Image (cartoon, rainbow over all chains, first blue to last red; front, top):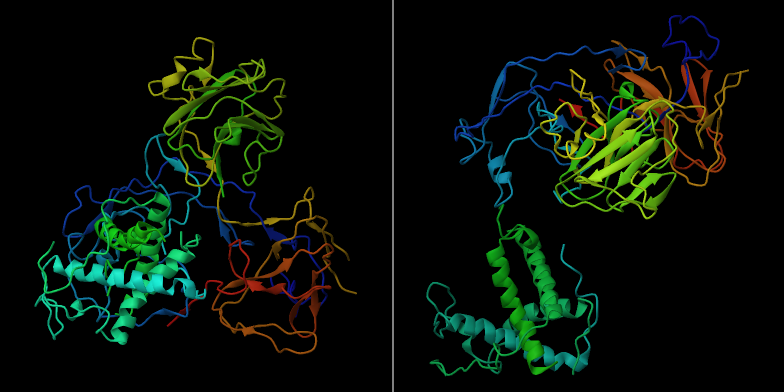
Amino acid sequence: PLSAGLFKSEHKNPVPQCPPRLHVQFLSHVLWSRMPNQFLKVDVSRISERQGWLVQCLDPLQFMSLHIPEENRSV
Amino acid sequence: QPVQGMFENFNIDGLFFPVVSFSAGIKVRFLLGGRHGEFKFLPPPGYAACYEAVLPKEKLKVEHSREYKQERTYTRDLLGPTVSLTQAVPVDTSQIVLPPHLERIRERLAENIHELWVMNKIELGWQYGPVRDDNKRQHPCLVEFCKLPEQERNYNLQMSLETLKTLLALGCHVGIAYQLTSGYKPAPMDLSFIKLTPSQEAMVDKLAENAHNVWARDRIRQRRNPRLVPYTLLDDRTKKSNKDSLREAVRTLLGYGYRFRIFRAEKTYAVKAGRWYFEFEAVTAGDMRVGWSRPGCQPDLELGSDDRAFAFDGFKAQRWHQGNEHYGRSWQAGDVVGCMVDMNEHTMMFTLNGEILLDDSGSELAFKDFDVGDGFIPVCSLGVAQVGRMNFGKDVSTLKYFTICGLQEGYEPFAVNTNRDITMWLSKRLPQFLQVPSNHEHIEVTRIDKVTQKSFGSQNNNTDIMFYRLSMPIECAXXXXXXXXXXXXXXXXXXXXXXXXXXXXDSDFEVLMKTAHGHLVPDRIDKDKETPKPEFNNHKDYAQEKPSRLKQXXXXXXXXXXXXX
């Protein structure tokens, strides 16, 4: 029945209130990314054969990703 | 056998390309034609291949689509933004009238082109005959202008008029200032004696460019030909040939006499005491700055603009702070520069290939009497098409100019006593959504509270478009999802209704006037209702609900869509 009454815990409140989480966010550019200290280390063919363009990577690599659900974003 | 799915109605704009994405434990093999790969099946009727899509006279190699995804040592070629590289029309000629005072000169130059195109054939020795063909070595255009009809005269004069039109439209006005044959002597004057000025050389060059451009625009209708490729990408040999063939005309004419990216160390490696030194190698010589920034610097502003960064540039040979002052000399392609900071004495120095930089005042150190603040982090900024390499120490065998200067003075590397390499925090390109800060200009948002509103407020002199968005989105899974935009008068607007389980976040893309009081209000009539209440000058602001979309530009169309089947 309301905007705020659909993405919160309760829904049977027909009163239009604004919780402190609802704050405007602008598409900004002041941000930093982190470069991993260990990449996938993939070699492609190193022979460049005539039977196709090869790529091969057997060494695995995993990392832990935090997930903000209210923003639906992984970091 | 094919699949039952295609992504129709998608954004046709952009440079598409084949791409594979693999996690680990993978052995993939793409298959092109020719020497690149080996086709095992047949292509669809008419569909070409990537081995033909490759540019002529260019080696095709595979590379990481994202970035320099090379698990290597510190000798990684860190690069900033890139130019378009021209990865994706003739000049206007007939837009000017034909003056009559040079119409005879145009006749004589057209007949000059005619006699040149016939002597081109008498080089091979063609014969005069009534039939037209090439392999038979004969040409019916061996008669002179008195007997030849005007339609073929018009066809031969077409090329002459176009080439003279481009010559006159090139920016400079052009006014007034034996052999055994069957009876024809092609010999207007001497050609090898005279010499063509470089101005006319470049003029006829652009003339031939335009000629080949219009020829290609005519040939694209007649598939995937090197001649169909534009003249700027044509083969140099045919370029030279066409160039001299079309420059013989001007020889005859003159004969008779008519987004930067900022990289840095991790802010937790801030230093407040000691002598620290780090190297920066620059392969190119474009826009590059290097230095030490406090742990509050902006990744979007130029390095060294505000007090939050102590930088130095080689593109202008000056140190970068609040203001500018000439310092040191510039570098070349493939140089190195070592930056030193003594925090106990508060001195900053730069050595270009061992030579300590010097200003006009005669002080070896760049900056003096700067507070330690929160520390200093090694930082560089690379503009468009730049290639650099940082070295925070940890490799003295590769620290070339460190043993020459700094080691005897008492300067130690940045990461000499370090076991794991630095994180190398870079400036990201994706413009994520951030909360409006209090200490910001031209973006001020209040909060009032009957109904609750979140009004806006601004003050500046430069206008632009902002992309405001709410914090929490609305999801629907898995029921009916329909987004309807209804105006105050009626619901006569664009209505989108296609979402299986998406989290549509409310947003408004607004333009900034001098006074912008447009805001968002959560109201209620029968269901969830958000009213983006605007104010005066409401003609280019949009308000809708959007999933994750992060693109900074200025458009309302081509918003990257798709429809699966």
